[PDB]
Image (tube, rainbow over all chains, first blue to last red; front, side, top):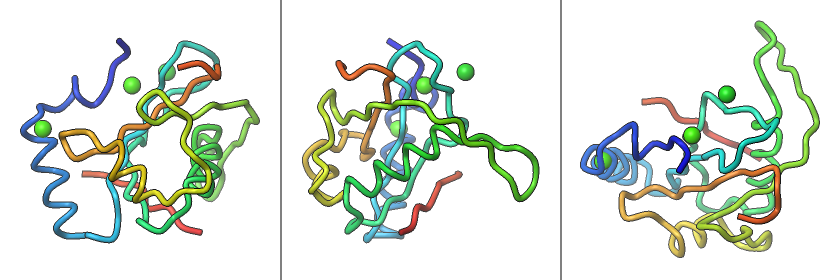
Length: 124
Length: 8
Ligand SMILES: [Ca+2]
Ligand SMILES: [Ca+2]
Ligand SMILES: [Cl-]
């Protein structure tokens, strides 16, 4: 029951956002990242991604690991602290050898977004 | 209106 984009933006606005972003950029998928448990993992301020359709899940997972563990340390600089992260799509582990389009086609939310979650634990 | 655009 943690705070998400659904609580921030109405269903009708989200549908409109994703529809026009998908018409404008048909080769990219809209992804929102959400924190799924309470731990030492930080809440990322930027959580909306427009991911190339042919990007591998394993590749996007690598990118997402870094993002979650990086914070701004001024201009030209980012501080990276190593932490173990587990990633989830619709409560399951994203399959590393798939395309990000596949995840989108399989687990896309009715509002048009692919919702993905991170946790410090491997469970849910 | 902000999106991150990841690359390879
Ligand atoms: Ca949140
Ligand atoms: Ca909406
Ligand atoms: Cl926080």
